[PDB]
Amino acid sequence: GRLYINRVFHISAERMFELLFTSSHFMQRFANSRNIIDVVSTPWTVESGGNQLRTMTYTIVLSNPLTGKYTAATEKQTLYKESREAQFYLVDSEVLTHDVPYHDYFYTLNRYCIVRSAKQRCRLRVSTDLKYRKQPWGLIKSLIEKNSWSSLESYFKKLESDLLMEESVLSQSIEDA
Ligand SMILES: CC(C)CCCC[C@](C)(O)[C@H]1CC[C@H]2[C@@H]3CC=C4C[C@@H](O)CC[C@]4(C)[C@H]3CC[C@@]21C
Image 1 (cartoon, rainbow, N blue to C red):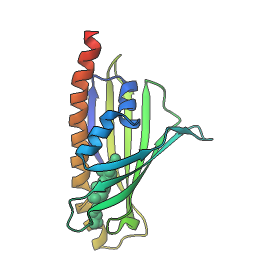
Image 2: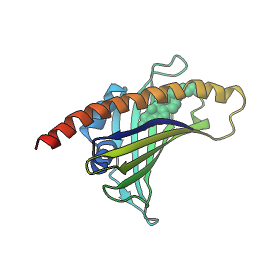
Image 3: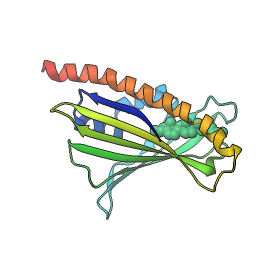
Image 4: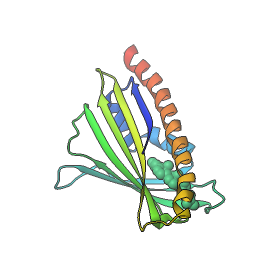
């Protein structure tokens, strides 16, 4: 679909994963700045396949005249079995909206890839794709496209800006010790 973040940070692959995929204060501050409230999540849970599973719910406060003031959302995060601690993290995040128009007809798939670059460095790669169900006809999908890609771009750029500010204070704190 679209590649929104491709960057090497001066944060370890371990710390980057715990920043993004645990109930970190970093994520709480970032979600608030994006008007995402009432974040509820699970711990990472193992299943028979070997992959790990984490699910979240939250409410997105919307600025769209075509939508209501709020929409419920559900996120299912899949950490693939191929991941190795502090070395390689590959998460597939599927996001469902529940109160926007045509919410039954599409969802979003975000793939997060964290690979350790050096000793305290990592490369984060986030790609985004829209998925469709029930075969939305004609005008429905073009409306979905024009009301998603720009909001997803705005979302992940603010995350990259916050990760860079995090990199600047965390790498300094580690280096100074
Ligand atoms: C047809 C037309 C009336 C639809 C308009 C309303 C749709 C929204 C509001 O335009 C949706 C579409 C994609 C939705 C985003 C998809 C993925 C994520 C990543 C996750 O971490 C945090 C929530 C977030 C940013 C979702 C936010 C809500 C988005 C942006």
